[PDB]
Structures are given as structure tokens and as C-alpha cells.
Image (cartoon, rainbow over all chains, first blue to last red; front, top):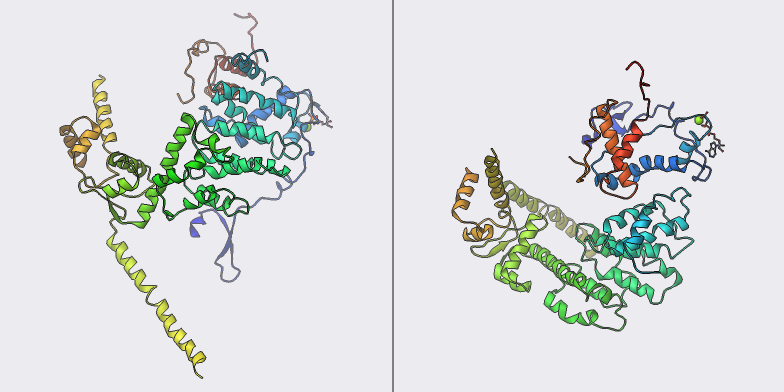
Length: 101
Length: 304
Length: 53
Length: 69
Ligand SMILES: Nc1ncnc2c1ncn2[C@@H]1O[C@H](COP(=O)(O)OP(=O)(O)OP(=O)(O)O)[C@@H](O)[C@H]1O
Ligand SMILES: [Mg+2]
């Protein structure tokens, strides 16, 4: 299916015939392989408290475009980009991302 | 409990659904409280409110393991919400999902009503590709033939199976009138203007089935024959076909000067000669090879 | 200067309605098309001749 | 022009304000006002999401202290 051979894809050539056997999606450069395979905490928003005004507001901006885009097509708005966590060390900031992951 | 004041309690709970989100979203009590206000908003004809507070509920799945009276009253409001608009396949998907939930307690009668709700209107949904596998999955089961509506279903599959709406309204009216059980039959058809439109849409779906069988099993037909075979006038027959051809769903072309609606197309001389040689090649070479080799194979069995 | 755009919206509204009566048929009489547009027959011909040219 | 507003309450008070506003911030306020209709299960501007979104985005740093005029 030569239409799938876009100019810049990755293929696997024969050793002797040198023709294309099977194409490949993309390299994943193992420096970032370890940046995916890890378990957060198996948490369920129950190891967190006193932050529910800020927890839900962060769950509002992230969970809606990845689940419910119909609420963003009915209103003439572009779905938003990411947020920021700032403050003194000790109140969440890692467990909160551990919750949403 | 004081009155059915439908304006005071409705707006005063929508202004507090934003409030107690801060207690964590518990699997039962939070879910039961958030389904309470949608049946209120269905009652005061606030349909824009109900479909959004119900759109949140899909993040809680597979919650029917511990309770059973949760998924029933959820879908019973979802079938009514999509009832006011069209798109009948979504009510069928909800009807099939309320078909296996009470049945786990071996319902003697409630299992029959959920069976009747599914099998009643599947033809009423639009036919694109999703009616095709749906009528292949809900049919051919061990427990469906207890009702003659399965024979009504099997008649409206395809190949016309000798269908006519005047014949259809006269033999199955007892199913539409009072019968033995007849409990979902009054619930869907035989009602106020909600039900009367469903007569028209059932009339609309059978003639849409009757146009598709004509365009496949005919080439040309006079317009007087098509009008009398659809039990309606010549003006409605033209306007109904004009609705289909601008919808690019039935592919034909009429004549209002001699009355010949034809069904084929002017074929191309490149296309026609290629289809000539293709029926020349695969019908006079492959089987021609086969005639020689079976006659060679009969040389062994016959002699000696 | 507004009546020029009114004429262009008028002539658009003719050719939008006069293409919804083309897909059902090849050969047709004209008096049905006059009755379906419910306007006239003479301006329909001058519009249809303009669309072919 | 694309977002449904359809209101009597116009954004005229929030035009001639001080504290000069970049062109990307108009997009951020109208998104944040859009979030404050959707989160509370509305569909239309109820003349308060625009003001709460403005008061959220402006709180960075402020008064000249009535000093050096
Ligand atoms: N708001 C909170 N609610 C519940 N537990 C918390 C909270 N904040 C911290 N903890 C506890 O702290 C630990 C996680 O530390 P945390 O992620 O808060 O550090 P941090 O704020 O990311 O530190 P730094 O900001 O220096 O990176 C967990 O064991 C958790 O029990
Ligand atoms: Mg940290």
C-alpha cells in the first residue's frame, strides 16, 4: 500500500535484495522510554483533601477535552491547553498529578 | 410534598449542584443525588438541562455489580429524553441495555416488556449500516418467537416478502388494539400526537423500504403503478421521491411528461464494453477450462 | 447602496430554489416548475437560459 | 461572532479600563467565561462569567501607590 509510504516514514529494507519489507511507525528514543512506564500510586482521589476547590477546577480543564468535546462544540470556544501548579513545597504538586495519572 | 411547585424546587437545586461537589464523588449517594434533578427538569420541559447533567454520568461505568435500581431509572429517563427528538437507534441501544439488567432475577413478565420494546421499532431507525448488524443480532435467538411481532420483523427484512401497508394495517391491528398482555404496545403506539407521528413514521419507513426494493428489482415503471402500489396519491409520491433523491440515498430519476421513473443510469461506452469483455472472459474461459477437465476426470470413473 | 445586494440576494434565491428541482428528473414540462416556484414562467425561462449561457 | 452571546449585557465597561491587555488575553477571558457557563451546566452568558474571568486574570501586580503621580 505505497500510499502509506509518506516521504519521511521509516521502513525495513532487505539485507540482500534491499527492497522494502515492512514499514515502521517511529523511533521512541529510549531516554524517554522510562518516562512512560511507571505506576503513580494506584490512588483514587481519596489520599487527598482540603483542596477540592482546586482539584475540581483542574479536573475541569483537562478531563473535558479528552472525554466530552460536545460541550466545547456547542459553545464557540477552542478547547484549552494545560495549566500550572505553583505554591510552597508540601501541598500536593506531585500527588495531585499522581491522582490524575 | 407541599405542592408540585415545579419552578421553585427546580432552580433551587441547580444552584446547589455546583456546591456539594467537594465531598468526593461516591459511587452510590453522589450518583443518586445527581439523577434526582434531571427527572424534575424533564417535567418542566427543560431538555437542555437534563442532557448535560446526564452527560456527566458516563464516567461511572460498571456500577451495576452491587446495585440494580440505579441503571434502570437512569435509562428510563434517557429513553424519554431522546424520545422528544428523533434518532431512534439511541433508544434501541437503551432498550437493549434494560433487557439484560432485570433478567438476572429471571423476570417472568418484565423480561417480556423489555423484549417487546426492542423488537417493536428497529426499522424506525435510519438504515445506514447500523440497522444491518442490529437486525442480525437481535434476531435468530432462542427466546424471541413467542410473539408474532418476530414474524412481523422477519417480513420486513428484505426482498419485500409480499409487503403492503394496507395489508399491514389490517392484519396486525389486533396487536395494536387490545390483546392478551399488550403492555408495551399501548406504550409506544396508539396514543396522543406522540403516537400518531409514530404511525406516520412507521408509514414513512415502510415506503422507504418499498422504494429500495423497486430500484433493485426493476428498471422502469410507470408513475401510475408506483402511486397505486404505495397506497397514496401521485403528488405525495413525487414529493417523497424528491426528498430521497436530494438526500442522495435512493439513486433514480423521474419523468413528468410520460411518467416513466427509471432506475438504471446511462452507462459509459468505456464502462459498457469493459463489462462486456468481463462477462466474456470469466464466463467463457474459466468454466471452459472446467468442462475439459471434468470430462477428463470422468474418464477414470467410467472406464473401466 | 443596499438594493444592489438585495438584487444579488434575490438572484441567488432564484438559483438556489431552481437547483432543488433538477435532481428528480431529466425531462420535464415547465408549467409544473412555474407552479412549484409559484411565481411566474417567463422569468424562470430567462433565469434558466442565463444559467445555461 | 462565533460564540453565542445574545445578551443585553455588553462588554463596554471592560474596554476603557487601565492595565493594558495583550491580544491573547481576550481569548483567555472568553474561554474562562465559557468554562464558567459549561461547568455550571449553562449554555449562555449570564452576565457574570465575563466579570469573574476578568477578575481572575488581572491579579498579578498593581498600584503605583499614588506616588510620583
Ligand atoms: N494536600 C495533601 N493531602 C494529603 N496528603 C498530602 C497533601 N500534601 C502532601 N501530602 C503527603 O505528602 C506526600 C507527598 O508529598 P508532596 O507530593 O506533597 O510533596 P511536594 O509538595 O511535591 O514537594 P515539592 O513541592 O518540594 O516537590 C504524600 O505521602 C502525602 O501523604
Ligand atoms: Mg514535587
